[PDB]
Image (cartoon, coloured by chain):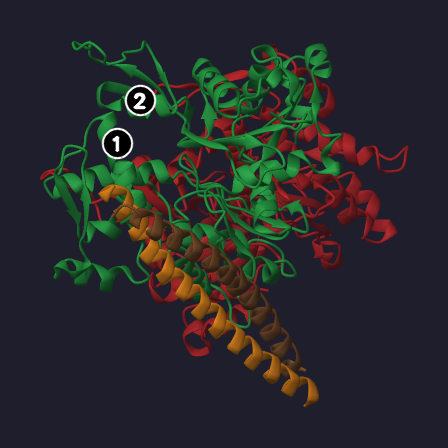
Chain colours: A green, B red, C brown, D orange
Amino acid sequence: DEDETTALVCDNGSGLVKAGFAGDDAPRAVFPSIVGRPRHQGVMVGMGQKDSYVGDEAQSKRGILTLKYPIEHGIITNWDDMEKIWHHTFYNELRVAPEEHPTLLTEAPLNPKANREKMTQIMFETFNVPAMYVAIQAVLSLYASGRTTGIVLDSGDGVTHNVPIYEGYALPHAIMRLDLAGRDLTDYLMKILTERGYSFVTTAEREIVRDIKEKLCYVALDFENEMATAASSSSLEKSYELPDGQVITIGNERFRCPETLFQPSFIGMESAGIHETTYNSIMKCDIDIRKDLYANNVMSGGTTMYPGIADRMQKEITALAPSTMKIKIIAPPERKYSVWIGGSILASLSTFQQMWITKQEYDEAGPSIVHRKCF
Amino acid sequence: DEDETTALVCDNGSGLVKAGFAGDDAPRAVFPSIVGRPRHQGVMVGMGQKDSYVGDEAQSKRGILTLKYPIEHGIITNWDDMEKIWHHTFYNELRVAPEEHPTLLTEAPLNPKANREKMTQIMFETFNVPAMYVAIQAVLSLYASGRTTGIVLDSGDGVTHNVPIYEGYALPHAIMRLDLAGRDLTDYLMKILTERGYSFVTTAEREIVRDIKEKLCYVALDFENEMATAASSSSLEKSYELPDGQVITIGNERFRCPETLFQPSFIGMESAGIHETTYNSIMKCDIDIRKDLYANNVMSGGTTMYPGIADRMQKEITALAPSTMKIKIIAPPERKYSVWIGGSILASLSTFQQMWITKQEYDEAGPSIVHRKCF
Amino acid sequence: LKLDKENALDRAEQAEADKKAAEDRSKQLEDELVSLQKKLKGTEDE
Amino acid sequence: LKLDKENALDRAEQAEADKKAAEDRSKQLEDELVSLQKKLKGTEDE
């Protein structure tokens, strides 16, 4: 439906995937990064029943499906499932066949190399895309957030990357990658809700909990005082209606789960928490850099959408930070959708039209080409 | 368990502690500089679990512990943890303690003053040592190498000092302090192994990587040739079995990490590289000194064990050095253990018996005495 | 009820549109405030 | 329609509450921005 060969853009996380065309300010469609498969045989007539379900199809029929996420802590390990996701995403919802349009995909700065190689290879060999470009999520976060300098906390579903950037440059000596992410918060919430009498153990249940988390949970600006209150009074409880008509409420569990970001030991991770991890990214940088990073702490990705996270993070960094310095967190409405938006911005920059791998260079060099052409 | 009325010697860094008694040619034992603490709440009864672990206990149980290292780029800041490490070292494992013996501890020549003040104080006040002496690692490195003259390349766990001595005298303006050592190389390898699909984030994982590095990595005499092949073919890869049943292979990363010593920019460090710092420690000395330092380039500390480092450092300096003159590197089996050995030599030399602070002079003067009696 | 999801939705969308204009002003004003405060402190330090 | 009204309404009320918060935050920041501008003019003149 496009009148120009605009790039198509897809931000494929370990959780959800956002897609649209370059030049827009939002994805046109959002899908989970899921290919679903039935674990049961349907009995009734008129119940659909597929061998496999993709994206929103996997969620709609999830009650009897195993829901597999092809991306593991930022890396695609199942390329067949990503082909199903990209065919559906580009061809059915964006309504564009990649054969006539270049495509931009994204990965974290320390994302395993095989990810960028398969993202590039799949689009060139299965979809015949005329060109490819694997973007840096840190760049995209900054372009969506209006910054060139700052701390990128991309808090994704599979990993929190945590990288300081100055004047458009990476400061790699200060990257503190953390294996604590949105996926662990969903798993932890299934377990804490179980403590309250509402057990969630299946894949369908995982998605229910994911929805509960997104609407009911928060980190709290003061964990211990909020906890003591929530544990003492119903005034901090919030209800949710489950698909079968049952009602679940969450008390101090409402924040004890999100608190895992600040206390990763709750899921068994060895870490000082998201705020020390973030701080580790601002003090390790040079003496004439630190001041600019403190004043430009940038959120992108999801989990940034907890009601109290921008303010608690600003407070925790301020507490760890030296005096005089201004500490500020940028937490735009483009939250969780920011990396996709940055992808749109990058794909269309005039300064980035020479960064694309063509389907000439690709075939002459093979899949490893992404290593020298992208970043 | 020992009945020899001699001095005790310890080399304490950000990674390891070498220790034993003076007069021998080797440490009796080597301990990690670690005080380990549980990072999990125990559930079952009868599972042991200590409140703290020391040295090798902390490393052996690390899968469920957070490991703290008391020394920061050569300076002890967590004196309480070093007291625990020293108690274990001396009382439990070396089977000899300072209470009945004079004790020598080491530090780098430009190490902040507080380090030597606390080392002196803890042995006198918590271990009741009859005497003390804080030694310069450069002194010890040349004694253990059979030299009075030479360049000491003391590549430790947290710092490389790069310090010349001529005829037993310091040439301090020619010291090239470098913020690159074995611990930074381990952190870099964790990041590039993440690039290969094997993420390492936790400290237990850091210890796994340090083991991989020590057994699989090298610098290479010719980096570019090894790199071009290793980056292109599996014939240059070497396997390591991870303690979870996975096998990791490493290609050009096998040498890119160690290469950081020659190219510090790999980890974001502003430095000319170890071979230029070596060259400058020689070049910044007077012209009737320079020739003797070129002929007596002495390795000490660890990282000196990488294949190609003794041949490469000699190649890199001879390539910068003038012709006719002979450039030589000293790199004995006592590599990495030579500072301890030098400590043994200094502590036991008859020419050094007037250099000891007794617990007479110390008690009247206090810890500032280290600046009157040691250096 | 018939038009109330529409009345509520139009209120939600109008309020969201105004919220955003005001949230964007809040961010602009806060960034100017912080920079201005830093200018203030710059000059106060001077 | 109750579900659509309820969703539109939670959004209508939250959006109105949030637009009010955005207007109040942008108003307070504008007033504080002005106080900082005046205090800055003060430090610049001083």
The label on residue B303 is none
Q: Earlier in the sequence, mark 1 or mark 2?
A: 2
Packing grade of label 2 (10 A; few <14, some 14-19, many >=20) is many
Snapshot quadrant of residue C25: bottom right
Tell me the element at label 1. helix
| Closer-to-camera residue (D16/D43) | D16
Q: Are marks 1 and 2 in contact (CB under 8 Å)?
A: yes
Tell me the element at label 2. strand
Q: Chain of mark 2?
A: A
| Closer-to-camera residue (B251/C36) | C36
Q: Residue B162 at x, y = what percent?
A: 68, 48
Q: Residue D43 at x, y = what percent?
A: 64, 85
* Distance between the alpha carbons at the discs numbered 1 and 2: 9 Å
Q: Residue A2 at x, y = what percent?
A: 63, 27
Label 2 is placed on what type of residue? Leu
Snapshot quadrant of residue B125: bottom left
